[PDB]
Amino acid sequence: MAAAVRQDLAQLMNSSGSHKDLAGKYRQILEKAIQLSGAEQLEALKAFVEAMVNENVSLVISRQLLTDFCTHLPNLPDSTAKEIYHFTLEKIQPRVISFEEQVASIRQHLASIYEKEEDWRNAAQVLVGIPLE
């Protein structure tokens, strides 16, 4: 069902309702993305992340749901968590000045999946990228 995710996210990109009307609808598609299974889940989340970083989707919507997105990936296995995390860190890279609270929390969960699987190199290199000071 990875064809009604790009459909529903597209129409809400330009609406005429308040933040409660739109942020409530967008988080309902996060349900449609996470509930998928196999290799069909893997592309529906990529549709969700590109819509948030989009310039046609407001900044009040982008910092609200990428917070909820970052805590829905500790649920999934280490094969899908690491796949989707690296997708979220190079679509937020074009505008890394805006979502630094997301870039901080996303890169921390990524370094834990690395170290777990005997990766003592790339876990560190991701924490270097976190713009602390």
Image (cartoon, rainbow, N blue to C red):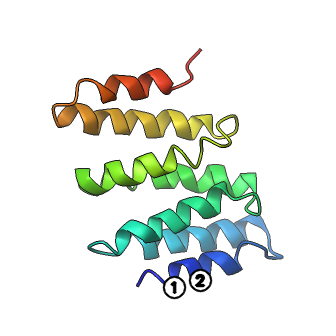
User: For the point 54% across and 65% down, which residue is it?
Assistant: 48
Q: Which residue is mark 1?
A: 4
Residue 42 lies in quadrant = bottom left
Residue 14 lies in quadrant = bottom right
Q: Position of residue 51 (x, y in %)?
A: 63, 64
- Circles 1, 2 touching at the beta carbon (< 8 Å): yes
Quick one: label 2, few (<14), some, or many (20+) residues within 10 Å? few
Quick one: label 1, few (<14), some, or many (20+) residues within 10 Å? few
Q: Quadrant of the C terminus?
A: top right
Amino acid at pointer 2: Gln
Residue 105 appears in the rendering: yes
User: For the point 53% across and 74% down, which residue is it?
Assistant: 28
User: For the point 59% across and 83% down, which residue is it?
Assistant: 7
User: For the point 51% across and 26% down, which residue is it?
Assistant: 130
Q: Residue furthest top?
A: 133
Amino acid at pointer 1: Ala
User: Does 19 sit left or right of 64 as displayed?
Assistant: right
